[PDB]
Length: 244
Ligand SMILES: [Mg+2]
Image (tube, rainbow, N blue to C red; front, side, top):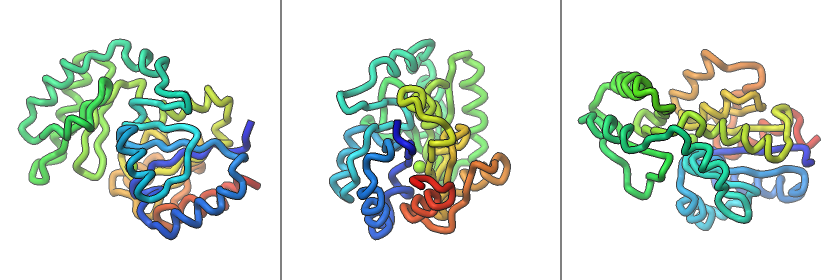
């Protein structure tokens, strides 16, 4: 029932430029009831709450955490979404395969969850290995999704997961339209957002992979901001004429 569904990544997007984070929040603060806010981060829910304390993030209506792996409503984790992503998902097999790549080192155990297997690519390893991994995983027949961001982070998620699939899910839940939705991102784990038909903005401080994506798929609903971090969001809101 609100006019805007604002979805944004936290690190290097909403957070990063404290001054811009603050004037973006002061603005939205005076029209708080006109938009649903959702943070789509690659962080765990707990990691995200921590960050909120650090920079003073405004309380959102939803948390699309761990790259869309888990969705937290105000009353708690969405168990429907979890049972939805659990179908045909076989983490142990995908992990066995992934663990076999010498160039891949597992990320902290706390970066993992039932639907997210994450690693770090060796700075000296050839990126093309990611292609090999993807292909090998896809052939298992298990609906798997490979997310590579900052030329270093690798995430193995269910095909149904994604920041974008979570976003679409949310739009369904809130009965919001793509034309009423704005997605903001900076890296490869945000690509799923722009794959969505919502209005999207790419921050200037965006990672190579995302920019590359834009040069090939960048559509008219996708805006390349002049500003970086939170500033790109105010810029985008003025661009698509949201919160008229
Ligand atoms: Mg990101």
